[PDB]
Structure formats: structure tokens, C-alpha cells
Length: 247
Length: 13
Ligand SMILES: C[C@H](NC(=O)C(F)(F)F)[C@H](Oc1ccc2c(cnn2-c2ccc(F)cc2)c1)c1ccccc1
Picture 1 (cartoon, each protein chain N blue to C red):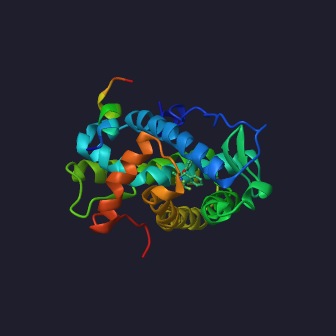
Picture 2 (tube, each protein chain N blue to C red; picture 1 turned 90 degrees about the vertical axis):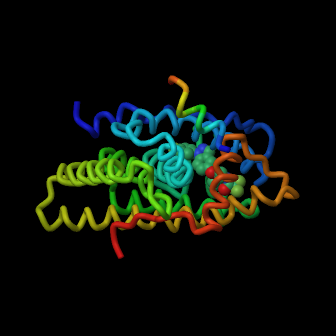
Picture 3 (cartoon, chains in turn blue, red; picture 1 turned 30 degrees about the vertical axis):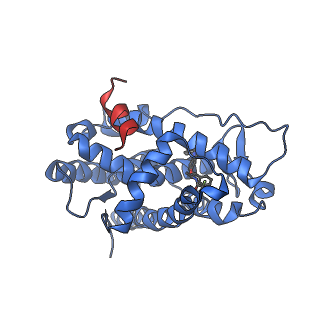
């Protein structure tokens, strides 16, 4: 069984928001539902990561570390792919029963957060990212940031990350282009991976503020509250090394 | 600290 096929079989199932369309929309209502849905996506993301070959071989602390750093990167990227495949328009397919379209995009403060997610689906559509390239890239996003002083199993992590970088290269070569076109595609896809750090920084700026300001009454489920509570001090103590392919 | 996440990583799926 090929490595990319083992990443394919563990793709998480499509979760529904449980959004009542008979009651009118509001930003608060949509954001609350999406946060609750996001908690369920993150619980599925742990099950997913545990089945990634090599992930379980890292120290338990490194497994926790990587999921906590990469959570929004994984979600933005999985959402971008889902949106790119299902609509080809300025649409965010958070769930089959909860699609963020142009009308929903005009709701107060909806766009300022949704635009970062739209950038992701826009870039996958612009670069015509394949399913195999996407699977390699998403596993690489889990391995995109480490602590300032590295991981407990740093040597093994560097070996696993190199393996998945080689996997991305194999998915690119399958597009049957020449040596020059292949090198250009590698450059383009790793440039998009690099840009995910900025996409996430913008998402987290708004997300952290919303979580901390209790007067907004925006609820987060236990899974997300726990990740945000862990991550906020790490960012303020500069405890994050963001791995980049380019300078 | 990070009780849910450690539980999800340690339990058998
Ligand atoms: C925690 C975030 N909340 C906030 O930023 C806010 F706005 F509340 F502060 C929340 O994050 C997400 C991100 C992805 C999500 C969900 C729920 N489902 N998905 C998802 C759907 C399909 C996929 F393929 C992958 C993931 C929540 C979000 C809500 C609205 C707009 C942008 C982000």
C-alpha cells in the first residue's frame, strides 16, 4: 500500500452543522454553530492524525504540540479543499447544511474572517491542486510549526516531515509535466504552504479576541476552548517556530 | 492542562 493511499483512506467524514434554516441568519448564530462544528472537526482531526504513518511514533507531548499549533491550519486547508471541490464560486462549504454564500458574507463582521478562508479555496482553484497533492500538503500542515526549542522527538519528526515532502514531490510528478514545470509546481505549492502561516495568523487574531471577550457571548466547545487556552500563552511567549520552505 | 486532547490521543479509537 502506497503512502499517499494511507493518507487518502483516513480522510475524515463530512460533518453536518445541525443548522436550522427555518430561523433567519445572523453572524452570532452562524459563528456559534461554526465553533460548535469546529470542535467536532478537531476531535475528528485527532483520530485522523493518529492514523498518519509515523505520527504515533513521536513522543505523546509532540503529538499534542503539533495538533495544538496546526489546528486552524488543518481546518482552513480542509475547508478550502471542500469549498474548491463543491462550488468553484465565492462559497465556503463548512457543512452541507451550512454554506457561507454571498448573502451570508454581507452579515456584519462575517467577511473579515471568511475572506482568509476564501483566499485558501481561491489559491487551490488558481493552482488546480490535485487530490494527492492536497493530501500531502495537509499532512505537511500538521508538521508546519514546532516549539522554539524543538520537539522531544525532533530527529524522528525531521525524518517524517522529509518523507511527506518527498510524497508531495511524487504527487506533483504525476501531473506528467517536464523537469522545469515540476520544479515550478513544487515552488508554487510550498509557497501556498508557507502562506498558510499568515492565513492562520489573521484567523487567530480575530478568533483569540472573540474567545477572550466574554461580553460578545460567542461560545466555543471544550475542544476549541482547550486549544485556544493552550495556544494564547505560547504566542505571547514567542514559543513557536514556523517552518518555511522559502525565505 | 489539555485534558481532552491528551484523552483523545491516549484512548483506543
Ligand atoms: C474557531 C473559529 N471561530 C472563529 O474564528 C470566531 F469567528 F468564532 F472567532 C471557526 O473555525 C472553523 C474553521 C473551520 C471549520 C469550522 C467548522 N467546521 N469547519 C470546517 C468545515 C469543513 C472542513 F473541511 C474543515 C473545517 C470552524 C470559524 C468560524 C467562522 C469563520 C471562520 C472560522
